[PDB]
Image: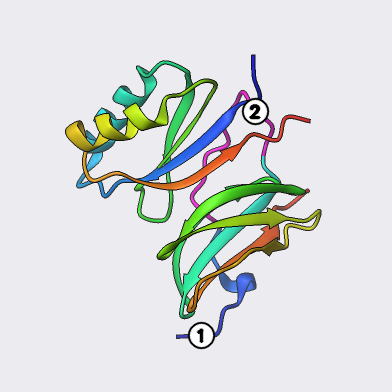
Amino acid sequence: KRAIDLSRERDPNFFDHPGIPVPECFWFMFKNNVRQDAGTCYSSWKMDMKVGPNWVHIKSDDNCNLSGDFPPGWIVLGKKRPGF
Amino acid sequence: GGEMQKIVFKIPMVDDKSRTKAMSLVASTVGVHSVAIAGDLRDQVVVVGDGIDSINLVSALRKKVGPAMFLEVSQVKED
């Protein structure tokens, strides 16, 4: 029931695939402040992700801030992984 | 070859048998370099490769593993 606080979120349950660069960011998807899932993604990059009812084009900046057209109730938030 | 693809599926998976079948099916698909099960619920199937027919792959997952949905389609940042 807390407001979204990435400092208190457990890390994503991720796998760094060995043949590609390690992605710099963790992402966390919430619906009305409840964590739905989490993963890894590249910084200074782009992806298409299913966020609730809609496909969303999400851009990441160099500090893992995520932007896109999130539908009502939903958000995807980023943060840099340790050491990046 | 080309810049690699990253495709993530969400597949409700009852247990580790289902997971094993999904990983085997994906690994046997043309173009796949690696596959892992990830996510908070252990139901994200993360696929990396080059020239994957994701159309056919989702169909095969739906027939053999469970009700697969796309979560993400992206390219790998290689530079």
Where is residue A28, by image quadrant? bottom right
Subunit under mark 1: A
Overall secondary structure of the magenta stretch?
loop
CB contact under 8 Å: marks 2 and 1: no
> Whole-Å distance between the Cαs marked 2 and 1?
36 Å
Write the residue at 68% across / 45% down: A42
Write the residue at 67% across / 42% down: A23
Mark in front: 2 vs 1: 2
Local packing at callout 2 (Cα closer than 10 Å; few below 14, some 14-19, many 20+) is some
Quadrant where the N terminus of chain A sits is bottom left
* Range drawn in magenta: A12-22
Mark 2 on the same chain as mark 1: yes
Picture coordinates of residue A34, whole percent (x, y): 44, 75
Where residue A20 is drawn, which disc sits there? 2
Query: Which amino acid, mark 2?
Result: Ile
Write the residue at 35% across / 17% down: B28
